[PDB]
Image (cartoon, coloured by chain):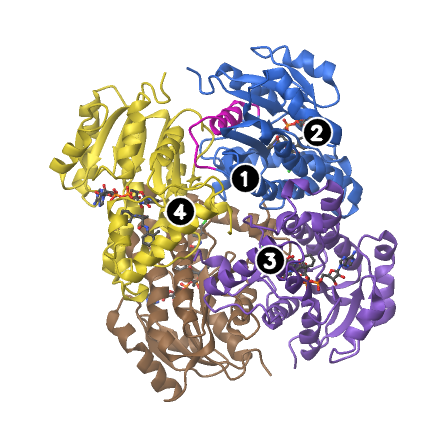
Chain colours: A blue, B yellow, C brown, D purple
Amino acid sequence: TGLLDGKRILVSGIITDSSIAFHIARVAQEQGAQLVLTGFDRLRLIQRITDRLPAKAPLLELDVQNEEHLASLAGRVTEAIGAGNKLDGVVHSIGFMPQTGMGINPFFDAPYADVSKGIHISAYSYASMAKALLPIMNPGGSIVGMDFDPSRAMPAYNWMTVAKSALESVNRFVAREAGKYGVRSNLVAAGPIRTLAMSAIVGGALGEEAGAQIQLLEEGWDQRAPIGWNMKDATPVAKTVCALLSDWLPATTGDIIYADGGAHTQLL
Amino acid sequence: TGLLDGKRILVSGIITDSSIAFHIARVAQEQGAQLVLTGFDRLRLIQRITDRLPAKAPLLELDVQNEEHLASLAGRVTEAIGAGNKLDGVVHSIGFMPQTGMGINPFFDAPYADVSKGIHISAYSYASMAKALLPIMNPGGSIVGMDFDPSRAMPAYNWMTVAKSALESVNRFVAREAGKYGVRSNLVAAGPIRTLAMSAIVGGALGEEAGAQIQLLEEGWDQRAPIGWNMKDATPVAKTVCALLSDWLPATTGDIIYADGGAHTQLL
Amino acid sequence: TGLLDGKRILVSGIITDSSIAFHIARVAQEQGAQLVLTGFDRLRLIQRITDRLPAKAPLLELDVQNEEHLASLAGRVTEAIGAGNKLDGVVHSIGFMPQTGMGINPFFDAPYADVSKGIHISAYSYASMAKALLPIMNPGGSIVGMDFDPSRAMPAYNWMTVAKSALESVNRFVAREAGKYGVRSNLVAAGPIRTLAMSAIVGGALGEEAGAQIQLLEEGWDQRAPIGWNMKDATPVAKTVCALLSDWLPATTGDIIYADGGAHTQLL
Amino acid sequence: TGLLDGKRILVSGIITDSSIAFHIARVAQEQGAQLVLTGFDRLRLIQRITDRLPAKAPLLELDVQNEEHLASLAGRVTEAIGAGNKLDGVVHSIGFMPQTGMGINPFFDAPYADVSKGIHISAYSYASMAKALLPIMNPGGSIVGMDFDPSRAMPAYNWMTVAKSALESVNRFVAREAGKYGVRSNLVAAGPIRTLAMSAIVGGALGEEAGAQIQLLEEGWDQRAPIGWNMKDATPVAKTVCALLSDWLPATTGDIIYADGGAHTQLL
Ligand SMILES: NC(=O)c1ccc[n+]([C@@H]2O[C@H](COP(=O)([O-])OP(=O)(O)OC[C@H]3O[C@@H](n4cnc5c(N)ncnc54)[C@H](O)[C@@H]3O)[C@@H](O)[C@H]2O)c1
Ligand SMILES: NC(=O)c1ccc[n+]([C@@H]2O[C@H](COP(=O)([O-])OP(=O)(O)OC[C@H]3O[C@@H](n4cnc5c(N)ncnc54)[C@H](O)[C@@H]3O)[C@@H](O)[C@H]2O)c1
Ligand SMILES: NC(=O)c1ccc[n+]([C@@H]2O[C@H](COP(=O)([O-])OP(=O)(O)OC[C@H]3O[C@@H](n4cnc5c(N)ncnc54)[C@H](O)[C@@H]3O)[C@@H](O)[C@H]2O)c1
Ligand SMILES: NC(=O)c1ccc[n+]([C@@H]2O[C@H](COP(=O)([O-])OP(=O)(O)OC[C@H]3O[C@@H](n4cnc5c(N)ncnc54)[C@H](O)[C@@H]3O)[C@@H](O)[C@H]2O)c1
Ligand SMILES: Cc1c(Cl)cccc1NC(=O)[C@H]1CC(=O)N(C2CCCCC2)C1
Ligand SMILES: Cc1c(Cl)cccc1NC(=O)[C@H]1CC(=O)N(C2CCCCC2)C1
Ligand SMILES: Cc1c(Cl)cccc1NC(=O)[C@H]1CC(=O)N(C2CCCCC2)C1
Ligand SMILES: Cc1c(Cl)cccc1NC(=O)[C@H]1CC(=O)N(C2CCCCC2)C1
């Protein structure tokens, strides 16, 4: 009697135990889902990480910039879940921007080759993955991607902000395509989560000013959030993704659900 | 093992079996919730209607323009659910605008006394009800109100649109207050639902042009919605309200969830 | 060869020499406009204030809660500008909320009678004034009102925020009506301007916490604004209103122009 | 005594006499501006076209994908306007998406190489051009780019919609950089303008369904616009760009001005 009992769900984006996708996978399994995981490049690492999940789940390789991986993905998923079975859910939890595109590196100095690679991985791939998986998704199914509200500019996030603006637009078009299959497509806009890399940025990995700016953003976020915001706790975000994967938001698509403590609704 | 197992939830706004709140109440009971209902003016009618719900629920009188009713409400609710028990949820499903404020009656001809009464009932009362009930709500609780997206003007909806714009603003302030209690506050923006009164408007009750315009809006809504929109089915809306009443959107507050088929995300 | 050469423009909302409308009137006259002014209650005061404007302008009494004043207004304006002449512009620079609706007074404690009076004056009156004046406006004309961005909640502004949310909605409907006359309707959303009353609030007139919160908002606004924000200078706002009154934004209506230093486009 | 008397303004994006930039250039010259034009690839054609403008203006080559052209641009502009003179304005009126990214070609079938080229030209280049020209812009100056509202998905516009979503985000970051120079950055979101290429699309150049869909969008736009919308008249758009280039919107930056008849403010 879990929220996702019987559902077959693909989850991308695990790379460490602090990955938002690790917590999405954990909560989905606690609620009865059967998972297929996808991982990029370091598959030995990812397998060792996902051994800590509450249940076993097959791990498939997927580099979203690799056309061969995308073309073979549905077949590999079907092999893993059994002929005649389809997916009920897909989680896109993938993002990347080269360091020239973030941090104290000036906005104008990011070469377009770098920005293009960030937009490929962070925005276009939401459409790539939907293209690959919709043919093996059931009616009533759900595609969910992770967003960070890009409606306003901010220090340091720079071209990643642009990539998220693109992703939000991509999501509204994926909803048009997915609708033909009876499938919903939505994003969860999360507040800041202190992953490994974010702690590295606070420690100055992308420059001192950038670290300082992110600490100020984190502090302000919890202040503005009427119910507070705990950057060390991804569980509320994971629960929100599972809500979208369930049968309980059946008339929402092309849309963005804010799991951010309510901060974006408050000026100060 | 229902979505709302053990939760005590107040539901306002039932007046007929086509009321959106009737379907919210039905689905919440199917998912294990224990309800207290509130009704306006025709309590004999409302009792006979709610006899058709799957489980029994006490009915309390509440005119939101009546200060005495509001001042006594928490005590009456506590009497109904038992001393030492509090509410986990509150549903505001209340709206009203005099006929001078809607339909073919010119926008400029609505007297302010009429508009004020519509705004009192449709917007201010969301704050009134929160004031009354927050002192008897548990941490983790949820206040939900019904919205119709007023971001753009449209024919005939006229001053009711203005009242909804006000309600959206009220909701962001109620979230600030509710947050002190560990309680969330959100609206569900539903697509058009063919209630009794809406069928009456399509039949020309507020003028012929108004009826024609609403039929065009309904048709366009289903067209734009990537997953379609069934104006005769309130269940998807009721499910969305129950999602917000559950524990599965714990980091959303001051916000608006669109249960509209995705229509507001598509231009055409 | 001023921006507004030959145009006849009604300007409401002057009460002191720090009124935003005083600066709108000054700049409009510097650019060639012929004005008619309207004033509320203290007409002797207002006349003495407007004697300092660069050119003479007739002053008419207008209490927007007074139906007789509204019903007679067009005739009084026509008397002042001459039979056979019409207005090219109207400026609404009127707002009010009782002190129970702002400041440290709790949001839930504002009586609806108070909120209703604030919404009447601050939102409904935009429609009242358009109703009164559209019959004596020329094609190509422009109605402009003053807004403070209410898209997010904030401390202390409380029910005035709600009134502005209502005003934004009203403006989109006034645009529908005005369009029949070839007239545009828009709002200017200004950043914070340190008028007499705002200095009084910073000095604690609506409670100490409220004053502290407004000083923080002011400081943050200038920080966020990419071109800065000078709360002591209403001229940039006045220029923006004159831009809307001119012939140079002929395809904008139902809309909001932000004269806020760009602050609403930046998170921090 | 023109709106732009004495101002030196760079205008990009002319390719035919139906180019929106041709009308921007014409109106700016009618209002006293001194222009420098930039053109892509067919410079003989562009020179013959711009011979029809009311005044002479030097034409410089600029392919925004060409790094050498960008690196040399400021020097070439300075050579054209005279050492010791700087620009007061820059107009970005550049867009491109390969045909795989628009029309009836399925959204999922656009190769990323194609999408990337569209985003390079249509979005990244707004930042490229600002980088190149800000060092030779005066305080009080203005950078303006052309937008088509991408807040909602729509048929056929497909990946160009995504590129515009990216451009809107880019504009908010360019505003941060430009602010250091005392320069504003804004976009004008225009309604549909029947250029040569758009007539070609209506005639079926990107598929029959796409042409049909654009005709429906055009018709609906004029219907929704409270003051109407004339797709054959770029002058209202050109005037709006000149308003932003003038001194009359001095507190607007990082923002979007809608020159669309008010259509985006109305649902129907
Ligand atoms: N951390 C936050 O503050 C935050 C906030 C809101 C949204 N998000 C978003 O959540 C998502 C997950 O981020 P995270 O914070 O968990 O970081 P993460 O580093 O743990 O996850 C990013 C993932 O993207 C994967 N990835 C990179 N290149 C790839 C490629 N070529 N093919 C496939 N996968 C590839 C990485 O392997 C990694 O698993 C991202 O979309 C991020 O933008 C993060
Ligand atoms: N029907 C739709 O298309 C639609 C769409 C979106 C949102 N909504 C909203 O959903 C909510 C419920 O509307 P509905 O369509 O179910 O209509 P409804 O008529 O069934 O419900 C409106 C309720 O408000 C109650 N009410 C009126 N005055 C009251 C007062 N003084 N005190 C207390 N209650 C009072 C009525 O008794 C009734 O129960 C409203 O907020 C409405 O604006 C409706
Ligand atoms: N000051 C700011 O920070 C700021 C920022 C953005 C928008 N605004 C808006 O600008 C407008 C003007 O405000 P201001 O700051 O210049 O203050 P102000 O006090 O100088 O102007 C408010 C005006 O409203 C008038 N008014 C009140 N009740 C009236 C009635 N019954 N009939 C007619 N007029 C009536 C007052 O006489 C006064 O002239 C208001 O809409 C305000 O909300 C102000
Ligand atoms: N036509 C409309 O309906 C409409 C509506 C809103 C916005 N817009 C926008 O207005 C702008 C101008 O479009 P238009 O309709 O006048 O079409 P247009 O074809 O006349 O202008 C597009 C211009 O981009 C130029 N361009 C393409 N690749 C380039 C490159 N590598 N380097 C430099 N310039 C390059 C072309 O030469 C051309 O001059 C675009 O941003 C477009 O997206 C158009
Ligand atoms: C919010 C912020 C600022 Cl202001 C400055 C720098 C960094 C951040 N926050 C992040 O980068 C967060 C949000 C986000 O999309 N990611 C991604 C995580 C995966 C690799 C690319 C970045 C991590
Ligand atoms: C959408 C629409 C148009 Cl366009 C014109 C007229 C009516 C409507 N739709 C409605 O009025 C719907 C949406 C809404 O808030 N209610 C309320 C139902 C309760 C009494 C007041 C109106 C019913
Ligand atoms: C921005 C702010 C906060 Cl946060 C708290 C209190 C006050 C304010 N700012 C104001 O009230 C500004 C903005 C505004 O509409 N007015 C109105 C001025 C006329 C009388 C009613 C208020 C003055
Ligand atoms: C609005 C629309 C639809 Cl719905 C479908 C197809 C085309 C369009 N409209 C356009 O493409 C308009 C708006 C726009 O950015 N351009 C650009 C003109 C320059 C080359 C790339 C496209 C022309």
Which residue type does callout 1 highlight? Ala
Q: Earlier in the sequence, mark 2 or mark 1?
A: 2
Task: Name the quadrant where ligand 4 sits.
Answer: bottom right
Q: Which is more toward the observer, B267 or A241?
A: B267
- To the question of a shared chain for discs 2 and 4, the answer is no
Residue D105 locus on image (x, y percent): 66, 47
Q: Is residue B10 magenta?
A: no
Query: Which mark is drawn over residue D211?
Result: 3
Is residue A200 visible in the rendered image? The answer is: no
Residue matched to label 4? B169
The crowd level at tag 3 (other Cα within 10 Å; few <14, some 14-19, many 20+) is many
How far apart marks 1 and 4 lie (CA) works out to: 28 Å
Magenta-tinted stretch: A232-252
Identified by mark 4, the residue type is Ser
Q: Quadrant of residue A185?
A: top right
Subunit bearing disc 2: A
Q: Chain of mark 1?
A: A
Asked if residue C57 can be seen in this view, the reply is yes
* Amino acid type for the residue under numbered disc 3: Gly
Image vertical order of residue B156 relative to residue A142, above or below = below
